[PDB]
Length: 351
Length: 18
Ligand SMILES: Nc1nccc2ccccc12
Image (cartoon, rainbow over all chains, first blue to last red; front, side, top):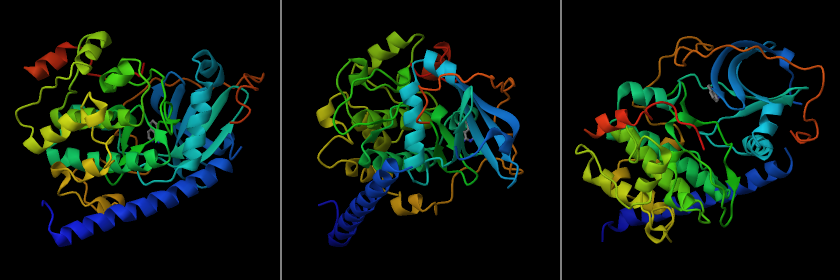
């Protein structure tokens, strides 16, 4: 066969150890999910806006008593209600409180006041993967593989907790000071033992079964991994067009084209992740995640060493001081106004 | 080229969720 006796026993043992880790990870998550005003605004100095979404914005802040820097996600409660994202917001906080994994951002504090909700998490200073990818053009296959392997492990972890992530893209991936990935946004993540049906995600990264309004499962995350690996290695995604509807037609078509510089191993991995047929998609078969981790394209990946953050990263972002923001774009600074009247108090009681 | 086509799509910047 492909493995001799020594490699075969080593791999089996490694896979078993993953099971034991994940079982313990699940019991820790569930304990924390079942039993979670950890600070206040005056405890931080607001430095600079790091990013904005429909919710509000993310600001670099310095915790005054300790001098530590953090990223503070500020959500305007009235905007959240108008956007119909109450459940998404409470769910994101609950996930962030309960998970623990080296590539998942760590929530330090959370609190709320009359007008806003606050999530204070570790500041990830190296910038968005998106910027780095667009600047560099494309990542070499070893560089893309280093990032991919972190997503594989992160999804292996999240899926064992029955969490589907559903919004993988370079825009949602931050680079930390050691060059490793951090995932921060969980606004579309959901606990899904079986199927779910919500149309959500980002056009270029949608699995065909979402587009086709089917009940779908965690395998949509493995399709999105295919799209991510493709985009990292090519510099552009496999399916693009002027308008989303044309992107969708391409996704569901079963056709994908590859750059001529893609290795054969990469193309084979991608044909099996970007597989429209669920009965054949890697990550969705009897062998589970092992079909991906054991694939030839990942043969040089030492999965434990990636997890332990013992692999030297191919790229280490520019790092000056602890509150340096040079790896982030400039955003327009809007003041954080706090109404004298409580807004949407009932909707956010649990936050 | 495919890259040129990507540029022509106009979806080269940060993409929003639906
Ligand atoms: N945690 C964190 N660190 C730096 C920048 C961010 C931008 C968006 C969300 C979270 C962030």
